[PDB]
Length: 173
Ligand SMILES: O=C(NCCCN(CCCCN(CCCNC(=O)c1cccc(=O)n1O)C(=O)c1cccc(=O)n1O)C(=O)c1cccc(=O)n1O)c1cccc(=O)n1O
Ligand SMILES: [Cf+3]
Ligand SMILES: [Cl-]
Image (cartoon, rainbow, N blue to C red; front, top):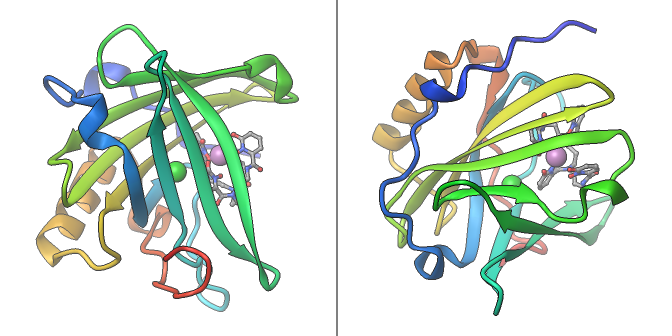
């Protein structure tokens, strides 16, 4: 395989004065961009949700809920606070096969409507990155959608690497 290079981290803003308590709760994935994200026209990606629960020790318990093969499935993982507020690493990284590196950075949010989060991982020696556009509801304005496209492009991703998952009612509500 070939891949679009991960951008340098200096091109990825960090949300100023991140407020971990305010960010918890359910977020819908209304946009998704990445070097392994690809528009499939015939089978469009379904919207999923991700729930952030802040723990006693200030890490997040993060649960994603998906509608796959007629059932809800739940992927749980831990985000451990990193170097600056709003950055995380993945907890228990040794329990993920082939995984050597994993970084999360909250790029911006207003907490009660929208967020943009950056992810970078190295698995089987390949460097993957993605940007997620989170919304407290399933719809978001054209202005936010365009802004996200603009941001995705600034990290080297073309239009065919950007997807807006289709809203669904099953599992995620
Ligand atoms: O390239 C990225 N993402 C787009 C492809 C997602 N996908 C297509 C859909 C898969 C369905 N699932 C996965 C849900 C279950 N979990 C996993 O099987 C998993 C295993 C090992 C490590 C890990 O971390 N996970 O999640 C999501 O829709 C889903 C929902 C919520 C959070 C989340 O993360 N995912 O993936 C891939 O499987 C894939 C294909 C090829 C390369 C690759 O890296 N991945 O992940 C990426 C770049 C940088 C950081 C990062 O976390 N990701 O995912
Ligand atoms: Cf992933
Ligand atoms: Cl996610």
